[PDB]
Amino acid sequence: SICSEPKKVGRCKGYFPRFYFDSETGKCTPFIYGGCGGNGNNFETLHQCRAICRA
Image 1 (cartoon, rainbow, N blue to C red):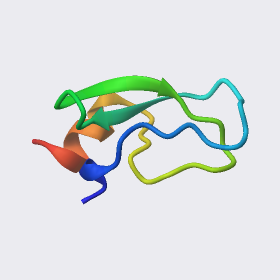
Image 2 (cartoon, rainbow, N blue to C red):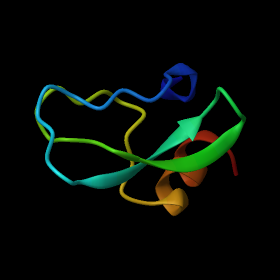
Image 3 (tube, one colour):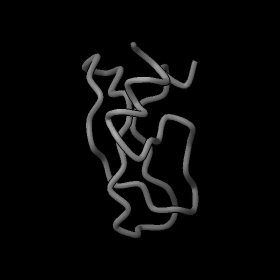
């Protein structure tokens, strides 16, 4: 699942703080997104990063 992606920002550098399932650590964790060039493992909240990947 999108669980498997690491953090990826994007081409755009806008300060959109988002959460990734930091599968590198096994955590949900914040990162800066930047709208343009996003990936799937990119969630508004720990709530979502959690719910979608790990109950």
